[PDB]
Image (cartoon, rainbow, N blue to C red; front, top):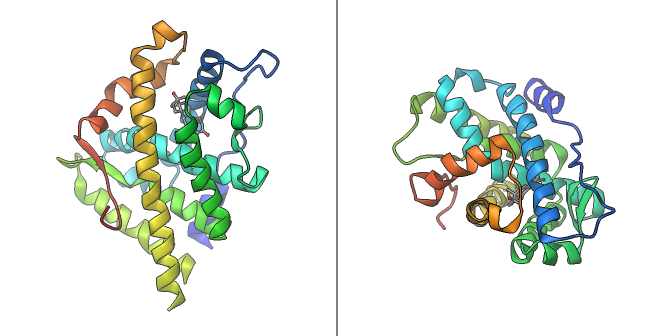
Length: 243
Ligand SMILES: C[C@]1(O)CC[C@H]2[C@@H]3CCC4=CC(=O)CCC4=C3C=C[C@@]21C
């Protein structure tokens, strides 16, 4: 009741990219649209996270940090879910006005990464993830990447993360054990994907001026300030099982 009531009530609604589907696809136009969509989704991720049960118990500085580190994985996870519920994972449903088909996957120069994300999407089907499990897993996904040196107040974070794990546990509840195993495995699988995208968007930002790919304000900031901390090993994901 209560926990899930909150997660359902705060789930963001549909977000459009504002892409112009009439002009021919192209590396520059597709990625620039994705970046605009990224900026827009970021606004929602922030509002969503701040409304999560117990989130404000975290030190104010830790709050923005965990959101900026988890942003990529969060977007990837929700996207895979939208792709599964809308186009049965046949394509990547980034937004109602920005669906990637085989051709866009290739023209965006993100084919292998898109293949990886499509696999994630398909897993929602293969595992028959319920909407409730999806919401719990997405929440937990927000608390799955932190600085090696710890946050301002690691204790509140560890406590909060532990609670979201217990919540996923209740929703699942020798079948419980098997289900918990496969869902935590799925959650772990998001990280390697998020890392490839972190590397890709970072490289893209550095040469964005040469390829005509625009990066909105807040994203350009996150990719140049928070993402390199992840790429250089200062910030690491928290895996359930050893990789
Ligand atoms: C194109 C790029 O710069 C590299 C990877 C892209 C990511 C891929 C994951 C993603 C999922 C969504 O549903 C919203 C937009 C979205 C992105 C928008 C811009 C990024 C960060």
